Amino acid sequence: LPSCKEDEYPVGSECCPKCSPGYRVKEACGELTGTVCEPCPPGTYIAHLNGLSKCLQCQMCDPAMGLRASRNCSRTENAVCGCSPGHFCIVQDGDHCAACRA
Image 1 (cartoon, one colour):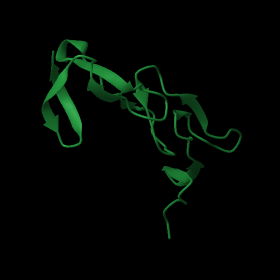
Image 2 (cartoon, one colour):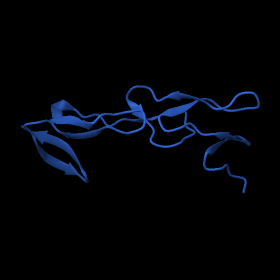
Image 3 (cartoon, rainbow, N blue to C red):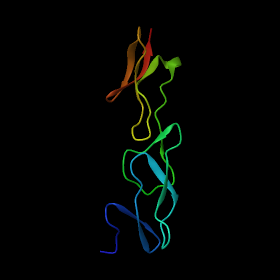
Image 4 (cartoon, rainbow, N blue to C red):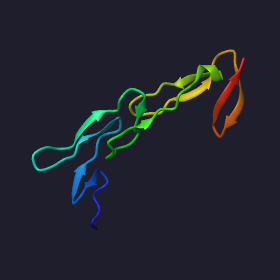
């Protein structure tokens, strides 16, 4: 097929190796240089091999909403929010809590 391998992504007619989770493309590969990947900036993440120039925005856990980061945001994993201690969940959105009351 014309498509690139799993490990790789298209840059016009080329296929370039992908960045590891935690990193984004700064320079596309060519004849003389490989893919140059930089770590996701503070506040963003990517859980997968990718060929993107940007990372995804991490989930904020707003303490004004009674929330605390139950898992911090890291280069390879979104933040997970839970209730601050002494607060209880007042709105559940699927498998996560969106707001807590004292």
